Image 1 (cartoon, chains in turn brown, blue):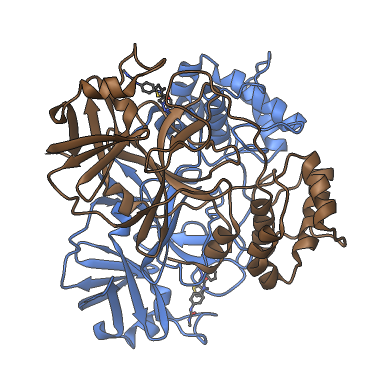
Image 2 (cartoon, chains in turn green, cyan):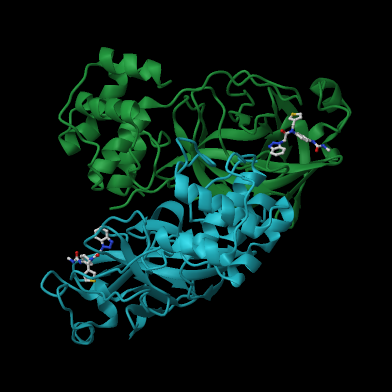
Length: 304
Length: 304
Ligand SMILES: CNC(=O)Nc1ccc(N(Cc2ccsc2)C(=O)Cn2nnc3ccccc32)cc1
Ligand SMILES: CNC(=O)Nc1ccc(N(Cc2ccsc2)C(=O)Cn2nnc3ccccc32)cc1
């Protein structure tokens, strides 16, 4: 028992982290096979960041200008190309520590682990969700760019995020591993609207089921609701509308606890309308939305 | 910017995890050099757990009864000994992945990362604090025993905890790597009093400084207090009394923010007396005590 904001073991990803330097800038790269992936803004200088012409900036760079170092050994760069907002640096050596991997584009509301790195060295690992508005609320300082987000299923790492930027509002933005930003963001030092965010309803319900499994049950009530009635409350509280697809994904947790999804919705409705009254659920005084139903099942079943 | 409950990268510890089987029981072991460390309760059966005579149980076991497997390779056991509540299984092969390490006994209120494992395989990593009452609020299922807690400074892993047991109250208990339990716990299936816990005052103040650094400042007020006055409030709210040693450890954060420690105490006093009024601090609606002052400095400075 017990429920924690658990990250995946980071070892397989630590083995892929390298340092990339171009001119005056140093950031992180991801070395998989004979390719190093990193944010293209590694080629920018102070005068560039406001509106960089990346094509022009990259044309002034040659293979020998990209300094890639894996621990204490220098990697030899034999090719470079820009794909969307990432640079792919071909190197002459395949990473001997390349795990089995995939590049995936995660959906908003899904979760993943971030291995925060500085100078190609890992500093820490934490779990987070991709917000409905495609930002992440991470912990990133200057130099953390190129740190990646991922999920692990068995021996396969699915890389889903590469860190690029902190918006002036303190929230974080980045790309999939093909360099496509999540959300409307551009890699420029400009004020950028993130857009209205909402709470991930299916995840709050999943975490309510985790609470019941782990013994926190005070919020369970004698009520039920419908998807329509619950969604009118979700509208009022800036929660994502719940769909039958969400109900279906909660099926395993509803079967394990014997609590129908709509009955759990009625508990969530009462908590939204009345607050926690100074009580806590799984050590939290707010409704947690960073655990997906799959995360709850995995942590409650001990998948390795 | 941003502040997260960050764990250490787990790679160095993943390389040390093995599976240990004795009779009908399977749990985790820690393979460092030519020794595998694991909870001694691996030698118990159903009839034993109520009050096991570990000396007698171990006398019935021989080296060949301890099945140790590192991934798919079997390790050969050439010695066994019990030290307090841990078994040390000498094997004929030194772990090639042994990082630089130390065994340390952490103090209550200090934090560490836990690599939850099942069948010698890592499932996840999370950060937690050793409560003032020497329990931990982790996420552990049956089979997680032998999972370890640790801190990493540069290239050295300081192992501080090995998981042994879940008390009937759902909280967790374990030992240092010499097999000495933290707290008054015994490795028996019996009801055991954990004792009054308190909130780690120095950590809440550290996290309040992290909030100010990261832009959450609404709780800062025009007041100050004294150690004496603050401790009368800490007494009322089951907080650890603050000492000058705690104030000294908060020095770096007080210098960085320009907010005197006693002024931060006055903010904490008002938050204890008035609550959060429905507001949040660093995404939390309660006063967080699982970040030490060193953790705040490290995460805010990006130490790798
Ligand atoms: C000397 N050059 C230099 O320092 N180059 C630099 C400088 C800043 C950035 N930018 C803006 C930007 C410009 C163009 S694309 C993005 C970032 O957002 C980088 N970033 N990401 N997470 C961060 C957390 C804390 C502080 C900075 C952080 C990128 C590159
Ligand atoms: C067949 N034998 C078997 O299952 N042996 C066993 C069975 C239970 C335990 N005990 C009690 C105990 C007895 C003696 S010392 C401790 C644990 O507390 C083990 N534990 N630890 N974290 C857990 C989380 C969830 C459930 C169980 C968990 C130890 C060994």
